[PDB]
Amino acid sequence: LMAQVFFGPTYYQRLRHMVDDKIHARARGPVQVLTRQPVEGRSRDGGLR
DNA sequence: CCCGGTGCCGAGGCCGCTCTTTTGGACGAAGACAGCACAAGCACCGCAAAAACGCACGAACGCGCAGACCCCCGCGAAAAAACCGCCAAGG
Image (cartoon, rainbow, N blue to C red; front, side, top):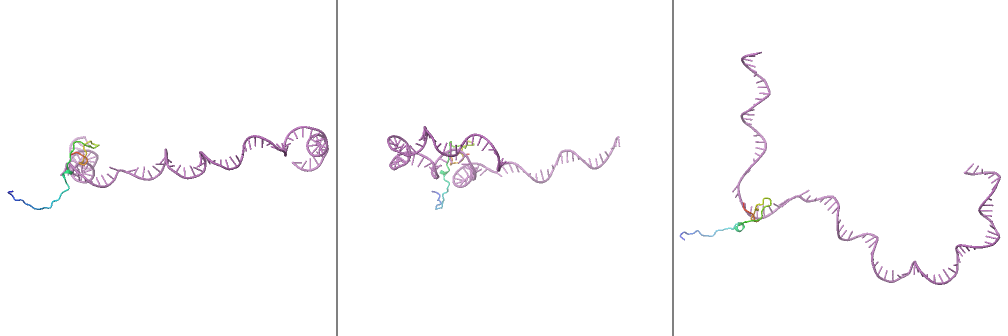
């Protein structure tokens, strides 16, 4: 490489936010009883606002 | 009674204080509440003392015989019961 590279060990930490705990998709599913709109929440297979 | 004027109710304008309404978007997870309890009736389980069924005894029923004694008849003696009457003392 034409440019030299800064290089060495550094202390890194893994945070709790992982993509597989955030990915969510919905085509159709449960709806609220009062308004008949998609429910809220990824855990409940909800929709996006 | 004409020229003029005052207080008067009346008039609108304006300043102050009270009420109302709203304050970014999206997403995630977890955790903890949701009236509720006390007094009651229809029905059940199971306990008190009255009840089931066998067995063996022997009591009481039956029958057959005995004869005692109770009923009934009789004739007369015996006696009270019945009848009649005067009258006194007690109700």
